[PDB]
Image (cartoon, rainbow, N blue to C red):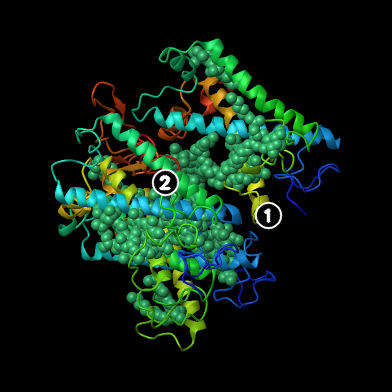
Amino acid sequence: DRKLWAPGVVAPEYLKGDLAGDYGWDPLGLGADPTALKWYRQSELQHARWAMLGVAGVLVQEIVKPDVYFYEAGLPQNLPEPFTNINMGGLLAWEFILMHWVEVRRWQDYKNFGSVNEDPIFKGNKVPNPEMGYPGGIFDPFGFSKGNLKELQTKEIKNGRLAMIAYMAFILQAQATGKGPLAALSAHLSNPFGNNILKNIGTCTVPHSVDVQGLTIPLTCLWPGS
Amino acid sequence: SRPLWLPGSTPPAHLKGDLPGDFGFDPLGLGANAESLKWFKESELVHSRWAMAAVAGILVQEIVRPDVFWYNAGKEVESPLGPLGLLAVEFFLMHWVEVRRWQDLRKPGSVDQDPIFSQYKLPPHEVGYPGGVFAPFIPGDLAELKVKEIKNGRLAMLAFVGFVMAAQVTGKGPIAALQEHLADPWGTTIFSKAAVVPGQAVAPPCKIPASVSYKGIEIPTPCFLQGLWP
Amino acid sequence: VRPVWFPGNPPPAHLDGSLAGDYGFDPLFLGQEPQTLKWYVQAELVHGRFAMLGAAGIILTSIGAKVGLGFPEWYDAGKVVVEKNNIDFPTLMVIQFYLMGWAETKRWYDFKNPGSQADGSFLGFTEEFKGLENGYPGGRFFDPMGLSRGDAAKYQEYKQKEVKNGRLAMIACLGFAAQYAATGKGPLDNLADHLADPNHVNFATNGVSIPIA
Ligand code: CLA
Ligand code: CLA
Ligand code: CLA
Ligand code: CLA
Ligand SMILES: CC(/C=C/C=C(C)/C=C/[C@@]12O[C@]1(C)C[C@@H](O)CC2(C)C)=C\C=C\C=C(C)\C=C\C=C(C)\C=C\[C@@]12O[C@]1(C)C[C@@H](O)CC2(C)C
Ligand SMILES: CC(=C/C=C/C(C)=C/C=C/C=C(C)/C=C/C=C(\C)C=C=C1C(C)(C)C[C@H](O)C[C@@]1(C)O)/C=C/[C@@]12O[C@]1(C)C[C@@H](O)CC2(C)C
Ligand SMILES: CC1=C[C@H](O)CC(C)(C)[C@H]1/C=C/C(C)=C/C=C/C(C)=C/C=C/C=C(C)/C=C/C=C(C)/C=C/C1=C(C)C[C@H](O)CC1(C)C
């Protein structure tokens, strides 16, 4: 648990280093209930893993093509060649049902741990689920677990938190200047005194609405000022 | 340890796997009362049987008469026996059978015997499950068929509302809507036809007129819940 | 130990936690007597019942408007159904007062005598108008689904949920009148006006709510 978030801070009582990435933190009291702390642990794992996917998508799609921009990459005009100008309703239907399966299976792993491990169609092999939020079994096709799980668990949480801050960076260094993360890094390395946080905060390059095949999306920045 | 509607869940205390089709699904607590659960079991059986007969009717009526449309099939049938003579015969012939079934529900050990052919009496059956003469040559296990009837019946209850909400949105019978979904799956869903965003709501247009003529006096056809649609 | 409307202040003595939706909100001590409180529980319930019916009425008939149907607004639906349908108006009012004077005086003499209204003096109904408790009549007519019997803890949950939805439907019905006396248009037109521009189309820019515009 040691080496806390600040040098002179006493850790809370419910943060004795059982969970990984535990730094005596929560200066807003949110983890003080245990049933709330397990759910907030699950949501930190969810935001961490989806944020790692977000970072490794945004800074790889401009590696493979630095023309399609990741902000408007959700527009049907910017989809690739076998999916260009697809009906987004059918795509949203695919995603809605295929995620309402998976997420409700994970949710019932939260609500009753151990009751959701079997393949329900093929009543055979289970998933060996050692602790909540870490199913494994078929989610470890390479078997990097069954070793020091605490070590890799701390590694996952630290890279995940860094990727959460990185992805909420990637959006805000794209709302202010309308430029991708490696492209904003190159814009900083061009002139590192007029292409910084100064004279870029205060403008919002996001348009107010974009017609996606008939729908207008409200499209807000996270600060005021266009 | 029976299978459930949601596998990790716990079924409610009033649902103990006794009845067929009991998969622990009653989240609103409607089957808590024991007296009311009998009425609800009877109405699930009757809704399910009418829905199975209706789904088979709409499908067979489409595969033998593709010209005429089942939502309009009560308008163009052109029977020789008049419009109201059909409704009078149906009224008396159904007000008989339904009061017989209702009196079976109220007092089960009351209504078995044929009143005009007194040598014929129905055997002491279970409520909702008459048998005897309604059921000749029953194949295999009666509890297994009693589960299969409720499963196919729940599927057909969902299928009839599927037929109605297809035929009010595309205006076509439920193979032609299936031919829409097989000719272009990505653009013939309900999420393709409709979406509501905070700032505008794109509902699908109606394919049912607000009235039909039908021999003088006109029948309003409410497009179910138009406006409340997505 | 129970949640209160104003944290910190203790709940008053006449208001221990046994009613549905109790949060200790009586600063004016109006229900200090047990029988006047017994009457105001009934009053809060039936105001909540009519306000839930009314709020669902306004919201459904305003989803009917603005989408394209022929429904009017809720402030215009009084005129359009006595003029589109040839309905003489004071007879509709007197039929409403007859039917609801019957249904209300039955309840008004259930409050004055709880075991009454059940002796078959009506058309042969004995247990159906028995009344389970204050503001929760039950029986075969007022609970045909039978949710007041079975699991009692879920019935207490439904009691508190009824009181919660009834409170915010009373607030909504107090708000529809203020949205109409301030703006002058439909409530779900006011919602889409607040959604098309979240700023500047709120109450503080209506010119009426704050006079210091
Ligand atoms: C939404 C993301 C999220 C969630 C749910 C959590 C949840 C948790 N974190 Mg965690 N964390 C996150 C992001 C998140 N973290 C990020 C991005 C960092 C890097 C700064 C950290 C760094 C961190 C440390 C160092 C530690 C934790 C710990 C904890 C646990 C106890 C604290 C608690 O109860 O908070 C519950 C949290 C919530 C209910 C979410 C509230 C969010 C508020 C409402 C909004 C945030 C304000 C603002 C918008 C943030 C700006 C971000 C932007 C500038 C990038 C809990 C499991 C402690 C732990 O592991 O103990 C076991 C611990 O020691 N976290
Ligand atoms: C109206 C027809 C109807 C009726 C009366 C019942 C009655 C019953 N069902 Mg059943 N069921 C139905 C249709 C019906 N079902 C359908 C269509 C499905 C498929 C989804 C199921 C699936 C199902 C399962 C999986 C289980 C039951 C069970 C039960 C029993 C206990 C639950 C209860 O109290 O229900 C009382 C219910 C009612 C009185 C219906 C109230 C209707 C309200 C007022 C409106 C509902 C609106 C609805 C959401 C609209 C859907 C629109 C569209 C999606 C179709 C009870 C005998 C359990 C059982 O068999 O245990 C014995 C059980 O495990 N049902
Ligand atoms: C596939 C659905 C299905 C299943 C499995 C059952 C099963 C059962 N029913 Mg049931 N029933 C159904 C549909 C079904 N029924 C429908 C739709 C109705 C309304 C007409 C009824 C009316 C009904 C009554 C009134 C009675 C039963 C009884 C029974 C039980 C014994 C009879 C038997 O062996 O049936 C076995 C059923 C089958 C093997 C299904 C064969 C289906 C064939 C292939 C024809 C289907 C297509 C056909 C063209 C449809 C048109 C026919 C008709 C509508 C004109 C058993 C539990 C009796 C009972 O409970 O006894 C105690 C009883 O008295 N049911
Ligand atoms: C959502 C609000 C709500 C809730 C949670 C309840 C809950 C309760 N009511 Mg109550 N009630 C309400 C609204 C509500 N009521 C309204 C608006 C009225 C006036 C019409 C009444 C009139 C009333 C009476 C007269 C009695 C009850 C009784 C009960 C209890 C048992 C019945 C039950 O569980 O209902 C469960 C409720 C639901 C599952 C929610 C309703 C389901 C759908 C979604 C509502 C949709 C509304 C629809 C759009 C418009 C329909 C209008 C209708 C007139 C046709 C329980 C405490 C009985 C009781 O306490 O017995 C002792 C009793 O005697 N209530
Ligand atoms: C999930 C997430 C992002 C996931 C993003 C994804 C999948 C992005 C996908 C895409 O980009 C690609 C790949 C390519 C694009 O073309 C398409 C899209 C679709 C756009 C970010 C979470 C980001 C989440 C973040 C940053 C959370 C930050 C929270 C903080 C810092 C709060 C801390 C505290 O609350 C605690 C924890 C405890 C309290 O006691 C103290 C305080 C301080 C209050
Ligand atoms: C988490 C997140 C998700 C965004 C999802 C979106 C936008 C989905 C759009 C999803 C768009 C979708 C589904 C579009 C669907 C279009 C469809 C169906 C097109 C169509 C139609 C209709 C409907 C007209 C109907 C007609 O008859 C047929 C047809 C074909 O013509 C975003 C978060 C943020 O945006 C905030 C909240 C704040 C920002 O500042 C920061 C970030 C973090 C970026
Ligand atoms: C009584 C008895 C007795 C004796 O003993 C013997 C005998 C005689 C044999 C018997 C009889 C019986 C019977 C009659 C039966 C019947 C049944 C049925 C009908 C079923 C159905 C059943 C049915 C069912 C399930 C159904 C299902 C359906 C479905 C899913 C559908 C779907 C769909 C839809 C939505 C729409 C779209 O667009 C398309 C589709 C895709 C098309």
| Disc nearest the viewer among 2 and 1 | 2
Distance between the alpha carbons at the discs numbered 2 and 1: 37 Å
Residue type at mark 1 is: Ala
Foreground residue among C43 and B215: B215
Q: Please name the residue that numbered disc 1 is placed on.
A: C152
Q: Secondary structure at mark 1?
A: helix
Q: Say which chain tag 1 marks.
A: C
**Are labels 2 and 1 assigned to the same chain?**
no
- Does residue B153 show up? no
Residue type at mark 2 is: Val
Foreground residue among A191 and B173: B173
Disc 2: residue Cβ within 8 A of ligand 3's nearest atom: no
Q: Please name the residue that numbered disc 2 is placed on.
A: B97
Q: Is residue C84 above or below residue A16?
A: above
**Residue A156 occupies quadrant:** bottom left
- C196 with respect to C180 (left or right): left
Q: Say which chain tag 2 marks.
A: B
Residue plotted at (22% across, 65% down): A64
